Amino acid sequence: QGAASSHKLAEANTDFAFSLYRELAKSSPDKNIFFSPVSISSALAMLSLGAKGDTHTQILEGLGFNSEADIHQGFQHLLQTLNRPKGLQLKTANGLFVDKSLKLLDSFLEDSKKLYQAEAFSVDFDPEEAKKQINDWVEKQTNGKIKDLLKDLDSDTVLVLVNAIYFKGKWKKPFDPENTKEEDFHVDEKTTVKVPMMSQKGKFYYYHDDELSCKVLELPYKGNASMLIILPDEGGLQHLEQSLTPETLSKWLKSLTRRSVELYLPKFKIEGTYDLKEVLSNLGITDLFSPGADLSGITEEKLYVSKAVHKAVLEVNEEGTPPEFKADRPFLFLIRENKTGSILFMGKVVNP
C-alpha cells in the first residue's frame, strides 16, 4: 500500500546486488564476473508491470520487497537520476520482443516507456532474421559496443528480454601513460599473465580491513561515480566473497580515509553474459521463465519469458582529466553512483 520510499529502493537494490553477485560467483569460479545489478533490478520491475498472481510475488520478493509493495514510482525516479546529464550517460539497451500475433495491452506499452524508458517490440520469431534484427538493434543502441549479442534462437520463442550495457569511464585523477609498464598478473599459483600495469602516486580514500584481510580503495569517476576496488590479502578471496554483504560495504565506506597510496592497477577489459533464467532461479524468480507464467498484464494471451540475456562490458584504462595498492592478482570491484548509492556494477577480475 503506497509507492515505496527511495530508501526502500536503495536497500532492496543493494541486497539484491550482493546476492546476485554471490550466486554468479558460486556458479562460475575462476571466471571474470561483470554485470549491472541495477539494470537487472530494473528489467524485472518493468516485467512486474505485467505480472499478476504469484508470478508477481516471486519477482518483488526476489528484488527485495513486500508482495504488496509498490515500486514503480521509485524506480522511475531513480533511473531519472542515473540517466541525467550530470551523470554517467550510459550507452544502454533494453528491448522487449514479443511474438507479433500477440495483441499487447497498449497501456503496458505506454508505461514501460515513461516509467522505465525501455522499448518493447512485437516481432515475428522465425529463428533466423529475428536474431539479426535484435542483435543489430542492440548494436545500434550501444553505438557498436555490443555486437552480435544473441547466440541462437529456438523456434518456439515468444518473448525475448534483452538487457545490455557498455561502460568506459573517465577518471577524476588520470594515470600517466608513461607509468604504464608491463607486469606479471598472478591469476593463480600456476598461471601467469602479462598485463599493462597503470601506476599512480597520489591521495585516494583507502582502508586496510584486516578483520577481512584485504585492501579497499576508491577511484573517482568523472560523472559523480566511484570505483570501489577490493584487493584480498594473499589467497583469501574465497572467504572474502563469503563476507560480501551490504553491511560490510557500509563498514568499508565508514572506514575509508584519504591517504597517500602508491596505486598499481592493470588496464583491462572484461565482460559478462548471463542467462537470467538460471541465475534468478536460485533467487526464487522462477515462474516468469516458464509456461505457466502470469503476464496477462502484458497480453490476454498465454505467455512467459522464453529467453533473457543480460550482458555488461567494462573497459578500464588511464584516461583522463605510504601504503602500496598493487592489484597484480585476482580482485573484486564495484562501481557505485555517488548521489544515489546505487550499485551500477559489480565485478570480479580474474583474467584481465
Image: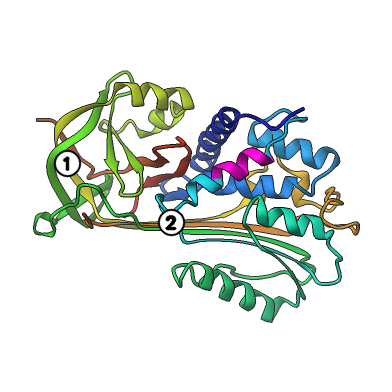
- In the depicted view, which residue is nearer to us: 120 or 80? 80
Vertical side of 275 occupied by 66: above or below:
above
Residue type, numbered disc 2: Gln
Q: Mark on residue 22? A: none
Q: Label 2 to label 1, Cα distance in Å?
A: 27 Å
Q: Is residue 219 left or right of residue 144?
A: left
- Residue assigned mark 1: 263
Residue found at the far bottom of this picture: 129
Q: Position of residue 146 (x, y in %)?
A: 48, 67
| Relative image position of residue 296 (x, y in whole percent) | 87, 51
Residue at screen point 70% across, 54% down: 112
Write the residue at 70% across / 32% down: 3
Image location of residue 241, percent across then percent down: 42, 32
* Residue 168 figure quarter: bottom left
Does the magenta stretch mainly form a helix, a strand or a loop? helix
Magenta span of residues: 72-78
**Above or below: residue 179 compared with residue 233:** below
Q: Which residue is mark 2?
A: 89
The mark that comes first in sequence, 2 or 1, is: 2
The three-letter amino acid code for the residue at tag 1 is Leu
